Amino acid sequence: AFDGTWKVDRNENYEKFMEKMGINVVKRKLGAHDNLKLTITQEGNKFTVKESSNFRNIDVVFELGVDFAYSLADGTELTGTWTMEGNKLVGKFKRVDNGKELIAVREISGNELIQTYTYEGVEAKRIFKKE
């Protein structure tokens, strides 16, 4: 599975995944239990994924692996690209506070949305709120 809707029901290693890139405490002020429909839409080599999280309601579209200096929710960036692998996104990276690997995946495999963002050996996931 993978298209449709998806969210971020829960969040493990999520706060510290954000933090490390430059995400200060302002997020601590209602910015963890929140966030939401990452949502996914399958396109011709792209995925207009939503991500109308608890803040910057919008959707993000990328022809599997495009480059955009988009700071992972207030940090500093996440250019490089992202992509999946049939059965699993990747988020990819090399934002700019450094040379990380957030790798905001989601993978998605049976009961899931393994957001699996492993910028440094932590990975932040829990899974969707699917919609």
Image (cartoon, rainbow, N blue to C red):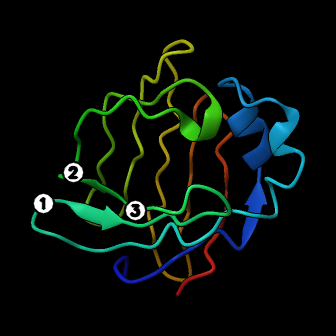
Tell how many labels. 3
Q: Quadrant of residue 50?
A: bottom left
Q: Residue at x 71, y 74 (%)?
A: 9
In contact (CB < 8 Å): disc 3 and disc 1: no
Residue 42 spot, x, y in % from top left:
24, 73
Which residue is tagged 3?
A: 59
Q: Earlier in the sequence, mark 3 or mark 2?
A: 3
In contact (CB < 8 Å): disc 1 and disc 2: yes
58 relative to 129, above or below: above
Residue 91 spot, x, y in % from top left:
42, 45
- Given the image, on which type of amino acid does mark 1 rest? Asn
Q: Which quadrant of the rendered structure holds the N terminus?
A: bottom left
Nearer to me, 123 or 27: 27
Distance (Cα) linking label 3 and label 2: 15 Å
Distance (Cα) linking label 3 and label 1: 16 Å
> Which of the labelled discs sits on residue 45, or is there none?
1
Which residue is tagged 2?
A: 64
- Given the image, on which type of amino acid does mark 3 rest? Asp
Q: Earlier in the sequence, mark 1 or mark 2?
A: 1
Q: Residue at x 38, y 83 (%)?
A: 4
7 relative to 65, above or below: below
20 relative to 50, above or below: above
Q: Earlier in the sequence, mark 3 or mark 1?
A: 1
User: What secondary structure is marked by label 2?
Assistant: loop
User: What secondary structure is marked by label 3?
Assistant: loop
Q: Label 3: few (<14), some or many (≥20) within 10 Å?
A: some
Q: Label 1: few (<14), some or many (≥20) within 10 Å?
A: few
- Given the image, on which type of amino acid does mark 2 rest? Leu
